[PDB]
Length: 118
Image (cartoon, rainbow, N blue to C red; front, side, top):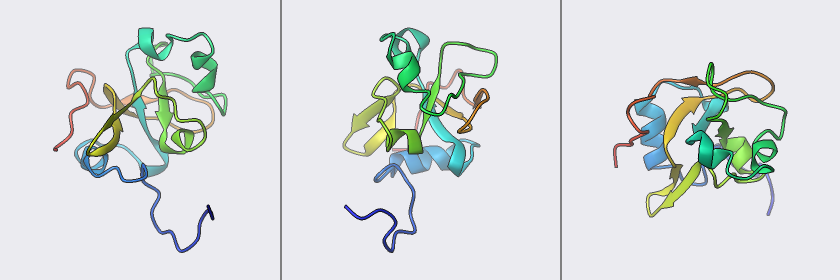
């Protein structure tokens, strides 16, 4: 357990499929996130505050589908919008780009269901 030792990668532990996602979807590395259906992301009343470790916001124009970033995943690991498959840690539903700090996240999918090439 030694952070930032010869590590030139900052992916989702593996990504792979999530990397194909990050290549197929127009987003940014330090603003890469996953957003889930509001009823599930907000399933827990504490979950709503759990995703906002840095006082962040939800989808741009849609207060409900909040997005947790890869850094947030290494901070808490919000399983509300994260799904696990043998391809690695991947999106649960909606893929979008979200800033760490304070502002909404932009969605470049919406109606694609956050699919990834294998």
